[PDB]
Image (cartoon, rainbow, N blue to C red; front, top):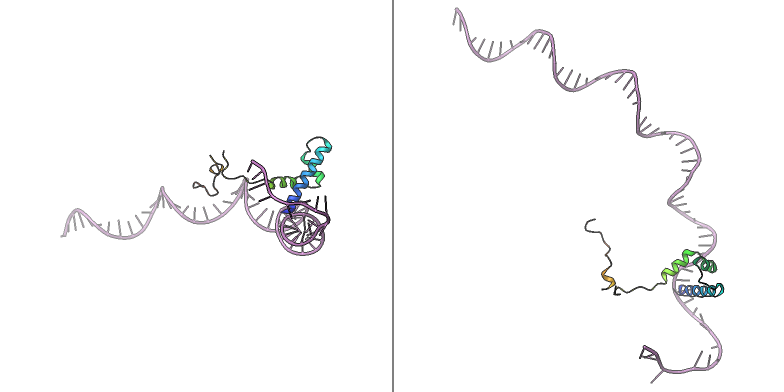
Length: 75
DNA sequence: TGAAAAGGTAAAGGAGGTCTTAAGCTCGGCTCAATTTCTCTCTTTATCCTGTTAGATGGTT
């Protein structure tokens, strides 16, 4: 959602501002405090911002190394 | 008529099942703290929608 894009942009801007102010890469807790949000929310945003990798990425393709969901004939 | 030859009867004894207690256990109920669901409120976000007035006007690899 658009609000998520705006949240990610604000997180990037805050991180750059803290890096400029403190002269070093900010930690997760520092960013979470500055954003006034829990660290778990920040990690959730970071995980949801990822781009999906295509199944045909060379490793040979990625799609030939992923098992299938089901009950093993043995089970 | 005498005599096998089988068929009964009354015991003794054993074999087997069925009853009785002293010892011990463990099992459920009862109480009674000590708590996890539930169901309302009561918020609080999560998601979508609309608008923005200097001027700008044909692609990169």
